[PDB]
Amino acid sequence: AYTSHLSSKTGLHFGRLSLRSLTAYAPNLMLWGGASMLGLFVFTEGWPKFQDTLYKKIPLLGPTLEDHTPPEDKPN
Amino acid sequence: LTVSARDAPTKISTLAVKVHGGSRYATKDGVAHLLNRFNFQNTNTRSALKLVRESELLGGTFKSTLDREYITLKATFLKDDLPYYVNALADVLYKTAFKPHELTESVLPAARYDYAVAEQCPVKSAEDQLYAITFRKGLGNPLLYDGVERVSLQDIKDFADKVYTKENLEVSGENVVEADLKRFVDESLLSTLPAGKSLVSKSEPKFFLGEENRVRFIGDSVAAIGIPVNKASLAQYEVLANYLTSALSELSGLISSAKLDKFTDGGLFTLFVRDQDSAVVSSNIKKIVADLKKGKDLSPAINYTKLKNAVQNESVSSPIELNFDAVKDFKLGKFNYVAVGDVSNLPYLDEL
Image (cartoon, rainbow over all chains, first blue to last red; front, side, top):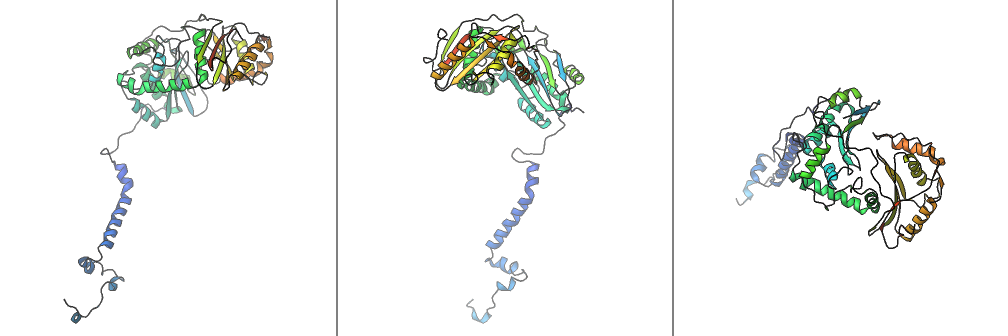
């Protein structure tokens, strides 16, 4: 056989990135999104709205966050 | 345009185009070096970047070399990409763009680098000075551009369409079938070149004997002798070269290099002794010429020089079939001399 030309065509890009960049990056970037959400999950554990809404719905780590003070012993 | 190829059952082929455009035929000196460094650049159709990138995707390598007679445009590829590289060499022979913006940016720094590299070796300076004192303005133009005579872009264009004519060039190659190469060189733009005159003239190029040049140079010192040889006495000096730089002599430990440059019309047998000390260059070249002025017998070196010339004419496309069996002896007559380096501690031509 004999190839007289080059039978090839441009990719999809915007100069700095391309689709081949994001295709190979996207599993590690969704893992980075999960790691960032985990980071602020652990950074906002003392926030009481996220504490009583989400951080006791955890199955076995739940009853460690609340501590059972009787209501007739707090000042407010 | 003579297409001369051969076949082999292998994978990698080469296609070469040889023009007669070295510094033998340069009008101003250094023009052929600028054309050789100028060769594989921007064509009027595609770039020097698109050609290199799509040929690397197709799997090949372009090159362009320059010696005293030819400019060689070589292309080494996988075997099933012949018509693309034929069309690429025809493109780059016909319609290079010749822009000043790439003359200053890309050609002149490469020429300056190649000239500095060939200057810092003290044996190439002796060799081209030996050429310049043997042949005055025939083969004795300098090989590389150095900024002495200012070369424009118009001189490069005039020399390029003087030398890139159809009767001047010929196309050879390894591992291509001759039928497809002769069918691809036609139906191309290599056939539509101007059919100018061929540039080679075949009578002997008017040498000069008994001349000396002394070049001052810091570093290591060389002493070179050089004999211009005819076409009939080419075999005796080839046997002499392969006898002198070989273990048959006792003069192989003194001679650092010795070689016969062959051409169509005649040749030049050159001999370099290089050292860092210079009294050893003086005593060595005195012993060399004082032993070569007596008669040496050259018939023991015949089988060895047949071997060496078979292995050196292996891959060249210009085989000269020398006989090597009318050779019996050698006695040195008159010879040109050039002494480069520590020049005051080197012997003159009257001392040798």
